[PDB]
Image (cartoon, coloured by chain):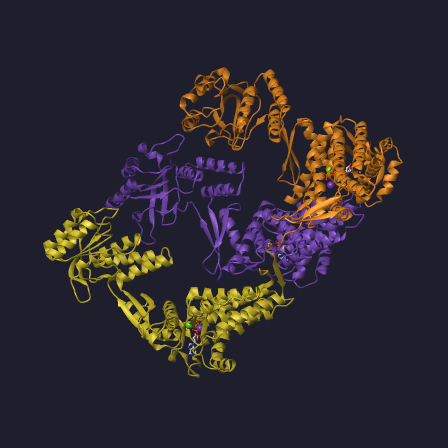
Chain colours: A yellow, B purple, C orange
Amino acid sequence: AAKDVKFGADARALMLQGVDLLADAVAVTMGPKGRTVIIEQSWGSPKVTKDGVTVAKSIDLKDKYKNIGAKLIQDVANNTNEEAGDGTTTATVLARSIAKEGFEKISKGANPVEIRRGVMLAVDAVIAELKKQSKPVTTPEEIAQVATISANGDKEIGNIISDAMKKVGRKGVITVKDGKTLNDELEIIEGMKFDRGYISPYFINTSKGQKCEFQDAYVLLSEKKISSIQSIVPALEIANAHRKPLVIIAEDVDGEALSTLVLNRLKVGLQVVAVKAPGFGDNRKNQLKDMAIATGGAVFGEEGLTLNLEDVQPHDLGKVGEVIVTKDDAMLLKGKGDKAQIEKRIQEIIEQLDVTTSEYEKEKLNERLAKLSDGVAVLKVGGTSDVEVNEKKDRVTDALNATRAAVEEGIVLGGGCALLRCIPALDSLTPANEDQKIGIEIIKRTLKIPAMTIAKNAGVEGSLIVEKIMQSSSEVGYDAMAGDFVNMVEKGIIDPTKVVRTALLDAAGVASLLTTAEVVVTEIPKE
Amino acid sequence: AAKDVKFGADARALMLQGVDLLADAVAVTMGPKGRTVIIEQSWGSPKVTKDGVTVAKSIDLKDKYKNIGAKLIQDVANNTNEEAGDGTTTATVLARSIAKEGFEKISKGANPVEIRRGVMLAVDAVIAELKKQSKPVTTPEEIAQVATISANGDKEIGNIISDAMKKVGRKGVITVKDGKTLNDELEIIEGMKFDRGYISPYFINTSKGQKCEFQDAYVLLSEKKISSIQSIVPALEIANAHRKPLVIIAEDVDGEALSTLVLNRLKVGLQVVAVKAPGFGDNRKNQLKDMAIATGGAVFGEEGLTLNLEDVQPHDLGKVGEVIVTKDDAMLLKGKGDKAQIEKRIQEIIEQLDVTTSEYEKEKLNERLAKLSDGVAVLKVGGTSDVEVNEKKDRVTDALNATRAAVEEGIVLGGGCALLRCIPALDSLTPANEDQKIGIEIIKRTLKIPAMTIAKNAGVEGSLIVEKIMQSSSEVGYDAMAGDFVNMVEKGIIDPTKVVRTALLDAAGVASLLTTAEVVVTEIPKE
Amino acid sequence: AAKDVKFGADARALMLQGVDLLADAVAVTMGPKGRTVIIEQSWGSPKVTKDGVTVAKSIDLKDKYKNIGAKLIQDVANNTNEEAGDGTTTATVLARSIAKEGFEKISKGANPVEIRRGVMLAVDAVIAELKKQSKPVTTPEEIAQVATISANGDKEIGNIISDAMKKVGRKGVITVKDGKTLNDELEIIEGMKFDRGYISPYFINTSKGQKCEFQDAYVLLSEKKISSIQSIVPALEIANAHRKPLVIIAEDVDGEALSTLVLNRLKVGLQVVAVKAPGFGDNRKNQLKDMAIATGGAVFGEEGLTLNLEDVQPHDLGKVGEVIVTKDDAMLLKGKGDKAQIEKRIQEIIEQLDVTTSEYEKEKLNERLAKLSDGVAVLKVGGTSDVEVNEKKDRVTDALNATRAAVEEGIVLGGGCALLRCIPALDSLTPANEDQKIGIEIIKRTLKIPAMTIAKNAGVEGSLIVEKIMQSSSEVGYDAMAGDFVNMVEKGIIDPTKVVRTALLDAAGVASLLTTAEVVVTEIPKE
Ligand SMILES: Nc1ncnc2c1ncn2[C@@H]1O[C@H](COP(=O)(O)OP(=O)(O)OP(=O)(O)O)[C@@H](O)[C@H]1O
Ligand SMILES: Nc1ncnc2c1ncn2[C@@H]1O[C@H](COP(=O)(O)OP(=O)(O)OP(=O)(O)O)[C@@H](O)[C@H]1O
Ligand SMILES: Nc1ncnc2c1ncn2[C@@H]1O[C@H](COP(=O)(O)OP(=O)(O)OP(=O)(O)O)[C@@H](O)[C@H]1O
Ligand SMILES: [K+]
Ligand SMILES: [K+]
Ligand SMILES: [K+]
Ligand SMILES: [Mg+2]
Ligand SMILES: [Mg+2]
Ligand SMILES: [Mg+2]
């Protein structure tokens, strides 16, 4: 395939045009007074979004040279989103600033690689200053404030996130889902709920709600399928001798045993119910073992130390205070396992979490830990249509990510003032040569961009706002929603440190390497 | 397919246009003050590179006559890269110089073949002079300096390469890999690590880290799969009699033996663990034998002198001071084999290396030698994004190749001064006729190109720099980064001899044959 | 498919245009001062060639009428290459001369068929004169001179070819192969080497080089596969009784016999090795029989007079002074067969060569004869890249073909003087009518073309050179490389007679028939 080659200023200008287009599209969404972007979808209704990475990923250019800069800015935004989950618009604007200022300074005598070295040095100094300015989060009010700021000033979302974190802990499992009503809802799931229904309608004993409900029930855990009458009769005899209900959690129940169970339930009133084992693969075994420790029972059919159903004993069965089974899910609430064994299992899970990490494995381990310790939380997002619901879920996810980041690390001032307060740290550096000085100056000029963008979206002159902020005391910043100068921490305009440093590092890392190019090679368009 | 034919000057001009385009694209990247090239990729983000062969391979031209010269220059760069692994930009610029000067001298009375003969004679003389000027490498400081120069002035890369060579030897196994952090890392792997995990989680005996760890363990090596209980029981009896752990490295472990192992481990505390054999094919047998000599044991199930598991004896088992097995890899650290047998095995491996050579076979033999003698080194390259990591891995690989070349042979001056100092050797030649004189003069003029290119990329007049260098003493050269005239060896601006001679030889060999053409035949473009 | 028809002068002019284009392209490569042609390849790097037939085969024209002449000239060149393997450029230029002069003489009253008859008569007379002027080759110096002239003045190629012919004979087997070094190499393979390696690594007994080496070994030749232990044990018993090594050359060795062999070799030190039979099909049987006569043994498993392995006797085994077996090839060096039987086998092979001839059969018979009599020679061609190596192999192959032709027949003067010295023979002919006189004059004018072309490529006026040559004594010719008038035979500027007569005959035969056309029919181009 034939190719086209460009040198120097023309190539730099075309790439800067692409970068400027993508960054201009992204920048309109930043701050409390930003606006939304509508993106055409090929299979239905368009998206309406206020999210930087979503807007960035949706733009592809016809010209081959502009698309290079567009793709690099997309890489910046995607890396920021993957690492922190928030702060992608800030990263995009910082990257454009660095790229433009770098391109403006290239000449015959310049050495772009040394300029890149100076840029990296300055960014390291800035990150050190940011880490020195951070403070830890200690109160639920700070959690609510962070969530409110991340959700674009919505107090209800912050309140619901704070309540969820209070109920399931600051490191618990919280998920976001679509709602079917006009309003948002918070649902707390306690105990062990594994989403498996009763095998046969004949086991129902509660008319209102169509539920099978038992109290003080024996639990029979079977790793392998139950088929024969010989393997099932002893458990029924044990249960009937003591006059207690029995819940059989097993891989499956076959025709003969199921027929015996239904016949006894119908003609004797025997209190029994059967359910499938949850999870597939080794996860099924892990869940069954977790239930075994939780209820104080044993697992039958294990490959190691195989325990036979034929000689089941009364002490091999778990005990649960309440069992609720319905068509879609089942729940055992109050097990009777030994606390020490449960704590040992929790310790084993949290140690396994630290050994090898993957999204699937981490998700499963966290779910197991939550089911065994504290429970899970579900936030249901409401709205009148799919477009509104998706738009609001974007903000809810941003708020959750920001709150987790602010729990892992501290908080700094919001509104772009945190980066403004790091400018004095760059005045202490002594560059080795002229190119590193150029890089340091590039970073020093770039550090003002976020506050100016926020002020510009608000309809005021950003440069005057930044000048007045820099002339005030360290605790004072600009409230763009109210349009005033206030004490940022007292008003709750705060940001996570991790998001800020991640955005700065990614933007600098990509833009400084972009500004070192001299030749660009592209493919000639096909017919 | 119809074809087009061109004669003489027009064809030469078109081919020279193609050569000039490709060489101009490549030349911008040369020296401490060179710049990068951005190459569009059809499946994602573009590449940013400062590597000559990568840039050369990426250019294809629409015109059929320019593409011929482009392909020839690509051949030059690819041959230089395959032979030395470094110095491709120098080869490209030398090839362009030779081609242009050769085309300028063709006339009615000229004989291009004799000009080629003279060019080859001059190149042979120059290589002889280079070999006379070389000096061996003796100190780690020279290794660090060579690595630093090859990595574009990065001192950390040179230091890490020097440390790796000190730890595993100047001819050990060093590999380059992607990192997941901001900084580069050096990892030394000792003993015998073959990347096979424990078969069953039941064998774990260490909670923190999820590891199976033993001290003073017996090792049972099985070439063939272990299935039956009779073949496995005797080894367990031998191990239990002496109260020692047992690690079974075998092709595989089947249901019955695995059940026995897990049952005994769980209900008795028997200290056992089992793992797969590493490598596939004859490599598996070779690895098993290597472990056998290393630990002083024997291999069961060999086709020749078959040794049966049923009559295993205490002296047929290896002994290892430490065994560490986890989900992904296993390691035996301190074997108890006889030193003489290990030395004999090493000698056999190094003799096999000299008989027949292939990339796969050489890689496997080197890995076996390293595992048995000294260990391996891994350099993990860090960065904020994939583009930066790839760009830096390019330089790390260049530095490794240059250091290996400089260990095989000596070193000469850098900055292009080595070829400048060979010009006086061409003044001693007596050509047989006029055409060979023309070729000698072509080479004499070409010998100045690298230094001029390095000076030009630095923003100064290259001809004056070369003139001042040639008027100075033999030890003085031009430092382009500082912009001074210095003692090259004291500053550490040095090059490998092999890279220089390889680049010169390849460039001359291809360009001199290019400059002998009179007719060019191409295919007419299709619709 | 519709067709276009042209008559007379227009068609002749278009065909002559095509002929002239192809011949002009080919002619630039002729003589010591010819130049090369670059041909585009669709799958990689272009070819650089100085070979007439390669250039001719690469040209196809868009116009349907020019392509006819181009294809006819291609036929001339291909026939010359297939018959003699050299002299294709001379044939091309002669064909163009004949075609142009024939077209110039066609008029209303002319009879082209009689002109063709006269051309053939003149060519027959010229060939008779050439055969009268030839002299046989007697000394190795003449061989070296012929090879040097054919290789475009390269003395090293001529020397290496002469050395190879001295070592393996003037009619031995010599092959040309790619080298992996900068310089050419000559390798002589003696004895019987059939390129089959040892079956099992266990048979190796020499560490340095990984070889299995034996002296004074028995040879067991088996036509059919060896599977059972009964068929193999008797040979081992016979070998062990006399304390001698044993090499088993067989179709294959199966599991049981191979296990016995490896076990005995490992636990007893029994000196044995086994190898596959070389060649496939009846060639395998022929090779096995050849080895049988060579070593004085017998072949087991033949369909006729089947001889059983179970009753093998000591006198049925061959004896070889030295056996060398490695991973890739095996060699038996000094057999002990009866000389009379070997001579009878050689006589049978050389008689079979004369009965039926094909390239495959002739190649196999020659290889068998060489392995049994004198050995083979391999010339490895060196270079820095594939293009140079291919370009040089072209010349090496030309030199080999020319030397073989000059050994079959005599030699004449080079530089085109041989055809110049045949002009006086055409002055003795008496034509029957005017058309035959026209043909004789056409040939007489054509006989000067090669010398004029050689002089023209050298940058001088060819007509004056030819005039001065024709005015000198018979032994004087023009040295174009030096640019002088010399004694051709003393300087070594000589040609094979066969090449000259073949080129003349083919060129005349095709061109004279081309010049008889009046109507041309072609197909109308498609869309
Ligand atoms: N009322 C406010 N006054 C001043 N600054 C504010 C106010 N509310 C939010 N900010 C600041 O605005 C920025 C938040 O902008 P926004 O959430 O749109 O962009 P982002 O986090 O960079 O990207 P993303 O689209 O991924 O959320 C943060 O600097 C926050 O401190
Ligand atoms: N500070 C310096 N001063 C002078 N010359 C230098 C300096 N640093 C490196 N050089 C010289 O620059 C050349 C290295 O250039 P570079 O590595 O870009 O090209 P290359 O090795 O020919 O190709 P490749 O792209 O394969 O690495 C060598 O001649 C080295 O001696
Ligand atoms: N030094 C020389 N002086 C004069 N004539 C020479 C000299 N060297 C070679 N020749 C003549 O040049 C001709 C060889 O040309 P060349 O080998 O290029 O063409 P060809 O044999 O017709 O074709 P091909 O391309 O197949 O080899 C022969 O006539 C040879 O006698
Ligand atoms: K936004
Ligand atoms: K470079
Ligand atoms: K030729
Ligand atoms: Mg946000
Ligand atoms: Mg380099
Ligand atoms: Mg020839």
Rendering quadrant holding ligand 7: bottom left
Q: Quadrant of residue B55?
A: bottom right
Q: Quadrant of residue B340?
A: top left
Q: Is residue A436 left or right of residue C487?
A: left
Position of the C terminus of chain B by quadrant: bottom right
Instruction: Examine the rendered structure and indicate whether residue A79 appears above or below residue C218.
Output: below
Can you give x and y, in whole percent of width and height, for residue C250 in the image? 49, 25
Q: Is residue B131 left or right of residue C129?
A: left
Can you give x and y, in whole percent of width and height, for residue B152 in the image? 58, 57
Instruction: Examine the rendered structure and indicate whether residue A470 appears above or below residue B362.
Output: below
Q: Nearer the viewer, residue A202 or B145?
A: A202
- Please tell me which residue is depicted at 16% across the width and 53% down the height of the picture: A261
Q: Nearer the viewer, residue B95 or C364?
A: C364
Count the marks: how many? 0
- Please tell me which residue is depicted at 23% across the width and 59% down the height of the picture: A197
Can you give x and y, in whole percent of width and height, for residue A172 in the image? 31, 65
Can you give x and y, in whole percent of width and height, for residue B497 in the image? 63, 48
> Does residue C2 appear anywhere in the picture?
yes
Q: Is residue A283 left or right of residue A128?
A: left
Q: Nearer the viewer, residue C411 or A507?
A: C411
Instruction: Examine the rendered structure and indicate whether residue B329 appears above or below residue C150.
Output: below
> Does residue C414 appear anywhere in the picture?
no
